[PDB]
Figure 1: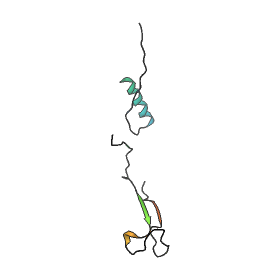
Figure 2 (figure 1 turned 180 degrees about the horizontal axis):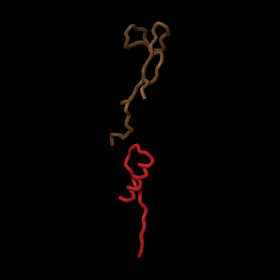
Figure 3 (figure 1 turned 180 degrees about the vertical axis):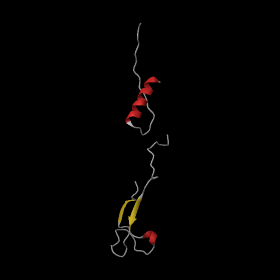
Figure 4 (figure 1 turned 90 degrees about the vertical axis):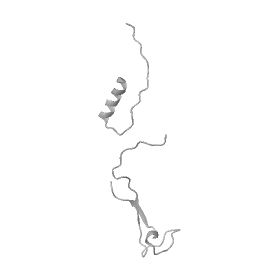
Length: 32
Length: 51
């Protein structure tokens, strides 16, 4: 198997969030 | 392009208040002497105390 990787820039939506809620949004960006 | 997202402000935005003591203090510079309540000279300012 040959594996390919690439760099991307990820964007979160704006708002006033707690630290735990912010970490959920970063994981959600990766999955999308 | 013409609106901005901000944190919710439950007080709906507080502004300042002005103090007047027309029979005790001299009028500060450029204020006119008068007896109309809505135009008394202003001797101090601060925020309306709601948080």
